[PDB]
Length: 275
Ligand SMILES: O=C(O)CCC(=O)C(=O)O
Ligand SMILES: [Cl-]
Ligand SMILES: [Zn+2]
Image 1 (cartoon, rainbow, N blue to C red):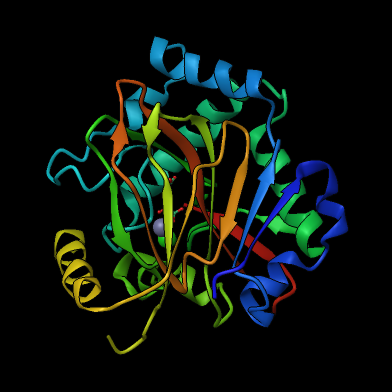
Image 2 (image 1 turned 90 degrees about the horizontal axis):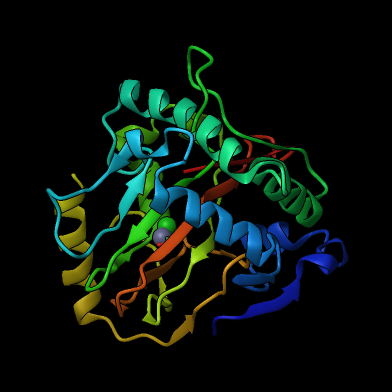
């Protein structure tokens, strides 16, 4: 039942209602957009991180050691699992934007490239949502997935019913939250995005959430598709509706991705993207 599209970033303007078709029409569920960022740009950013000349990106690195092998280490705080006050979230968001802008060196700039992609797929203006006191949300976060580590099965729409999304929920339309990511570094094997035909149910603590989803996902039978995008390719899929995960990274070479989420504004006149 799951349908994805394999298109190049040079033909995004040929699909002007893509985001509309996934969220509202539900005619197709995912999109793999090849060559959004060049391979050299992805190599240079990855090299900036591992060497430490990252514009202070390492200062907002969350090892997530309190969890198991079923989560990624993350550069900046992701909205998921944050406390409802968002004080730490908003401070890391500002550090992220600056450090990310520095690493990309406008070759192309991460924020404007991605925004021009979401705008090409909608025809609507693309913005990073603002907090209650005018603070910026982070446009994305960098997920570092080491050997033996994976991103455990979850569904995206569950996140907008959590206390951290209390303010953001009021800015968005009552519809499916899309999920996006672009690999910086890809592993030798593993680190695949496995998407299941299984759907989110409204009436059905991150440590508790991981254990709850896994126990319910255990019983249910579903169809699966696997995607391993290359460095610079965008994977824009209905992560809000469909249960998905990232398989165990095989080999010494780690998996590094820059991504987040996107959903329509209350009046469907704007696109909001964050992490
Ligand atoms: O690989 C990533 O960056 C996160 C994958 C994922 O679970 C998502 O995009 O929703
Ligand atoms: Cl998600
Ligand atoms: Zn996800």
